[PDB]
Amino acid sequence: MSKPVLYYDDISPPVRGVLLTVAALGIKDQVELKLVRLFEREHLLEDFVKLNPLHAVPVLKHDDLVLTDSHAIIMYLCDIFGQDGDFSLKDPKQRARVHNRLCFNNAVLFQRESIVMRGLINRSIVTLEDHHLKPVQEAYDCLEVYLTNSKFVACDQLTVADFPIVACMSTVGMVCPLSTSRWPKTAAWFETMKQLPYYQQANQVGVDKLKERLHAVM
Amino acid sequence: MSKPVLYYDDISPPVRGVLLTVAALGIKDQVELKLVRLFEREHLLEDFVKLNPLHAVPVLKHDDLVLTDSHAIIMYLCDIFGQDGDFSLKDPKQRARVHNRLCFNNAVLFQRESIVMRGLINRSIVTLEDHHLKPVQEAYDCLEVYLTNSKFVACDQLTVADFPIVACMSTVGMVCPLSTSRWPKTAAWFETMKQLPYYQQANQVGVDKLKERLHAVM
Ligand SMILES: N[C@@H](CCC(=O)N[C@@H](CS)C(=O)NCC(=O)O)C(=O)O
Ligand SMILES: N[C@@H](CCC(=O)N[C@@H](CS)C(=O)NCC(=O)O)C(=O)O
Ligand SMILES: O=c1c(-c2ccc(O)cc2)coc2cc(O)ccc12
Ligand SMILES: O=c1c(-c2ccc(O)cc2)coc2cc(O)ccc12
Ligand SMILES: [Ca+2]
Ligand SMILES: [Ca+2]
Ligand SMILES: [Ca+2]
Ligand SMILES: [Ca+2]
Ligand SMILES: [Ca+2]
Ligand SMILES: [Ca+2]
């Protein structure tokens, strides 16, 4: 009866990782959305800052629980809605495999992605030199290893760990594109992700919006 | 019978978050250590790079499971060794509260900490201007809110989420000290952490080592 409320702006890759998860879990009707538009600065309103001192999206509120990181939101939603399905995290080693890749997205891929994208968005960077994209390419190399050792990022099955990564990969891809030559396992995985039926609505919409803003800044 | 193996260098805050956890869980005898000395560049040896393409510590190997982020190592260890104790993560909301603060350490506190510490370690930064420490102070402000709303970082009880944060707080503290004036809840929490019986061995040893290296670079 109690519905989680997702505070979100789908231009954000972390948000889209959540939106992808909600869709894959089949719980779109079970999660209420509350738009928090970054470019309008609604994330700096007193109510939202009180909700999350990081003044960032996404945020999940469920009863009195407040999660302020897309990755914790994703694992929490798997725990309460996905325990008995294909995305289950009940097994401790499977849970750890998935969490390990969520950590990789949060602490490596999204960090390096964000540096570049925030730089362009706020005009701190004007020209992308190679040194801007080198950390992203190092993250691609790690991802290529992971996708050599298993079919998806965390194991041979799709898991929620694939969603934040693809959300990031489809963002920073527009400034640091994947080479099939250089990263064949990752390019193939990315195409497969793109074929998911909920990808268009849960991720591409927001990516296109961000592409509009990026073409405007460039 | 199967023992996890922890690849570690205790100058690293992520490592010390693990060491603190292993001690708090009372499982020092149950986790084998394997030293991987960063300043000797043992993390760049072929075997270790194959183990972890991020060439970073800590790493946990348990049977064929390989975790390559201190935060995933911590949750995994809680799951297999702490399920029936004071650090249990069995309840989904408690698990999410703890994971949410682990995310905060991984993606905010340790990121901003690491930027500064790596800068000094490799002499990219020579003088700490205020702009180097401003992001760290913003992270302190968030932490002060969290510790206003609960006695420890994630709830009113000590949890494993307190250990990575204190590991970071005791590192970047040496260049950006806490003010009791400015962050009273956090200063009090930090002192309490320092009083834990395993703090000296699991965290202070490594902090002191790093202080030696930092005085050498400065
Ligand atoms: N580690 C966080 C990162 C969230 C994040 O950085 N969100 C950005 C958008 S991509 C934001 O809301 N930025 C607004 C701000 O920083 O004020 C997560 O995964 O939720
Ligand atoms: N998010 C990772 C970060 C680990 C990390 O950055 N480790 C550092 C030491 S603090 C390292 O081993 N650096 C060596 C390198 O980057 O080559 C975790 O929490 O385990
Ligand atoms: O920082 C980012 C913003 C943003 C944040 C605040 C604001 O006022 C406007 C845009 C929007 O989208 C993003 C997407 C990214 O991939 C990384 C950073 C941002
Ligand atoms: O980058 C860090 C190293 C380090 C990494 C590689 C190397 O060759 C030497 C030191 C050691 O300790 C640290 C502690 C920190 O808190 C942050 C970064 C580092
Ligand atoms: Ca509805
Ligand atoms: Ca408007
Ligand atoms: Ca208000
Ligand atoms: Ca032993
Ligand atoms: Ca030696
Ligand atoms: Ca070898």
Image (cartoon, coloured by chain):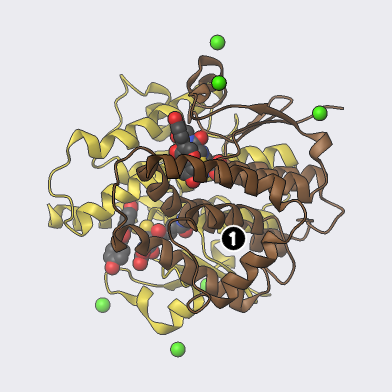
Chain colours: A yellow, B brown
Chain identity of mark 1: B
Which quarter of the figure has residue B66? top right
Q: Nearer the viewer, residue A104 or A217?
A: A104
Task: Tell me what residue is drawn at x 58 percent, y 40 percent.
Answer: A100
Residue B163's x, y, as percent? 65, 54
Image quadrant where one finds the C terminus of chain B: top left
Image quadrant where one finds the N terminus of chain B: top right
Name the residue tied to disc 1: B101
Which quarter of the figure has residue B94? bottom right
Task: Tell me what residue is drawn at x 67 percent, y 26 percent.
Answer: B34
Q: Is residue B202 above or below residue B54?
A: below
- Callout 1, which amino acid? Arg
Q: Nearer the viewer, residue B42 or A98?
A: B42
Residue A32 showing in the rendered view: no
Q: Is residue B132 above or below residue B186?
A: above
Q: Is residue B179 above or below residue A197?
A: below
Residue A120 showing in the rendered view: yes
